[PDB]
Image (cartoon, rainbow over the protein chains, first blue to last red):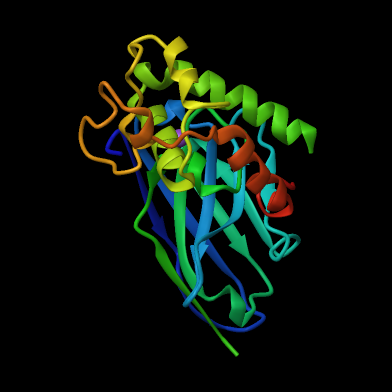
Length: 127
Length: 102
Ligand code: NA
């Protein structure tokens, strides 16, 4: 919805084992946001949650396939959430979406709790 | 977890209370009810206890065929009779290490 806008950047194409850092700039009525999440949709697969950050307490949540490799963090001063991605694998190739959830449900990596969505940024990792 | 169940039950019910108040909450529960083909927490009859929801009014997302205003003066044969909490909850329990771990 149009009360909050999310804009991703920092995508690109890298060789396997390399790193990227996605960023998502939030604007609009963002004081309502309880989770900032990163979702990805790989070629030929459904969208899945990758990482999420709860604004309430700073807690973070990760898909098992990215734990230890990816880190989500929030720069409050810039209203920007980041996804640091290390040790990238070809299976990490996907369109990555920034999303935001308001209060309601405490299921951080499930896209059904998120109301605001960015347009996505492409991450391509070469074998 | 039974924490996953109890919380989802509590939150879904609280979100039903906020459904009339907050159009984002409404959109969230709408997509849940439509996509999982369910209505209310235990049953569609749960909406009877929600303000702005009269008797015989459910969200349009409860309708088997979702058209604008279908939930007004609804017929039982035209709605999803199963509640969302057991149906979605079992799906959440089956996908828990992909939705909740830190
Ligand atoms: Na939300």
